[PDB]
Length: 156
Length: 136
Ligand SMILES: CCCCCCCCCCCCCCCC(=O)O
Image (cartoon, rainbow over all chains, first blue to last red; front, side, top):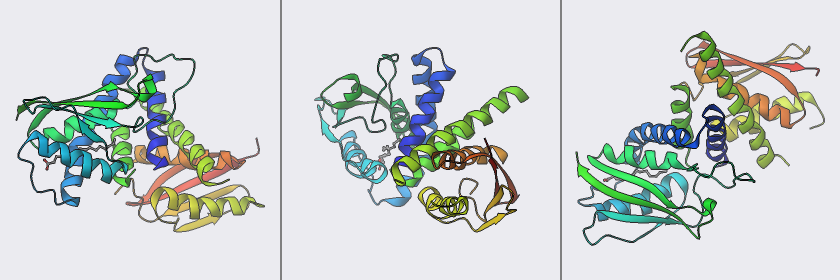
């Protein structure tokens, strides 16, 4: 949906005008994402019959194969599992929320789609999982793939 | 992108000072809407009348965004239109209409019309968007 993409791009643009530095933009995007994810989870659980995931591995499958599909129409691949099962990566073929960056670069520190990391954290907090979501690769930063690394911290 | 995402994002934008700061917030919401409205026309529409352009906003444009048409279109034939939506989706108060004021203004701008767009809740959840076409 262009509607969401365009709205999110306008938001990022406005935040960058509001804040002198991109780290403050990143923080605000994450906050907004967290608040969205808290609400999104109730939408998601009402729309699917995923059962319930009795580990981080089953949760990964639900996120990648069901939730991303539902909301973004895409299926990231899951890779790089830690032997302890508390860490995995979502690999995407581009940046999921942003198509283009402006040249020349004036936002090296900006995590264009940091809102998505907040969404992930907020939605999982509501199912009693303290997690961390973080972009570790981004095609918009010149990487081959986009990679979101997911870590399970604690149960709540 | 599923519709839920836009709905949640818009709601998160409107909720997060003094009257000046609050005013600035409204203007930011409208301005973001303006940019989105432009980009929507740019993607959607590749109009031999102003009346035609307003019909398009009420029909195709409102459907693209809210998945329904405007319920009533009124005009004074002197440059003011009123667009009525009997159940405005972003309600289910003023703050919640600003972005959409911009959507309309930005959509019109890309179709060659300068306008000033304002809105009110007529009676919840019904809303009226007033479009004052500018000569320049
Ligand atoms: C801004 C784009 C939003 C799209 C983000 C999709 C990821 C949302 C996360 C919700 C899925 C939660 C899965 C766990 C539920 C369960 O344990 O059964």
